[PDB]
Every structure is written in structure tokens, then in C-alpha cells.
Image (cartoon, rainbow, N blue to C red):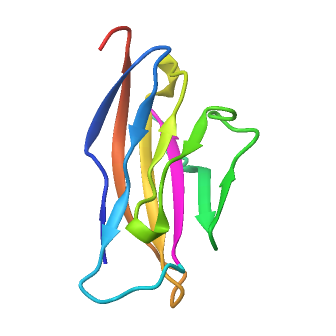
Amino acid sequence: IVVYTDREVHGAVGSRVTLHCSFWSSEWVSDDISFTWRYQPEGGRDAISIFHYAKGQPYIDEVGTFKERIQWVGDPRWKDGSIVIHNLDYSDNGTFTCDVKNPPDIVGKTSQVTLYVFEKV
């Protein structure tokens, strides 16, 4: 019922960063949960889906900004939906939203994290 990301993360160019996402519920919940990561670049307003996970299967977008640079490191059994962004570039700055969904609804719970990329870190 509650979704956790970091608030702000700093990455170095050429390096990598982990985007954490998890959730917790006071009531028991099944592993029939979906995670969706959307990306909104700095100063933009579109939230583009870069990653999805459901029915034990991950789905990485093959044409977007982070094609070939997304790694799934989550685990539905630990209620973890985290991903890693690889080979960072200055233009990767933006807001990432983790959207956690249950079977009984189409409406998820979301939490967001802001990424700034620096030359050194």
C-alpha cells in the first residue's frame, strides 16, 4: 500500500546508478504485482515507459532513450522492483516514476526519484 524510492540520486558519466523501488503492505499481498518505470526528461512533461515487469517476466523498451542500458535487479518475492541504468550520459537527467500495481485494480501507487548526472561523483 506504500511505495518507496529514493528522493534524488547522483550518477557519474560513463558509470551506472541503481534506481531503487520497493513497496510494503500491512496486509498479505500476492506476487501478482506489476512494476512500471516511466521516465520524464528534465524540463519535459511526458512520462515514457522504459521498463515493465509482470507475471514473473521483465520487459525492456528496445527503442527509447535507455535502450540497451536497463538492467532488471528486482525481485517480486522481496517486493523489490529496482533497476540499474548503465553507461550514463549527461542527457539522462530526469524524473523516474515507479508504478506498482495489484490484480484488483488498474490504478497503481507511484513514487518518484530524480537523477542528475555529473562529470565526477
Q: Name the dominant secondary structure of the magenta segment.
A: strand
**Is residue 109 visible to the viewer in this orientation of the structure?**
no
The magenta-colored residue range is: 33-42
**Is residue 106 visible to the viewer in this orientation of the structure?**
yes
Q: Position of residue 11 (x, y in %)?
A: 37, 23
In the current view of this chain or complex, which residue is farthest to the top?
A: 119
In the current view of this chain or complex, which residue is farthest to the front?
A: 77
The C terminus is located in which quarter? top left
Q: Nearer the viewer, residue 51 or 107?
A: 51
Q: Residue at x 33, y 9 (%)?
A: 120
Q: Residue at x 44, y 45 (%)?
A: 96
The N terminus is located in which quarter? bottom left
Say whether residue 34 is magenta: yes
Q: Position of residue 89 (x, y in %)?
A: 52, 18
Q: Nearer the viewer, residue 42 or 32?
A: 32
Q: Is residue 65 above or below residue 29?
A: above
Q: Residue at x 54, y 60 (%)?
A: 36
Q: Position of residue 70 (x, y in %)?
A: 59, 39
Q: Position of residue 118 (x, y in %)?
A: 36, 15
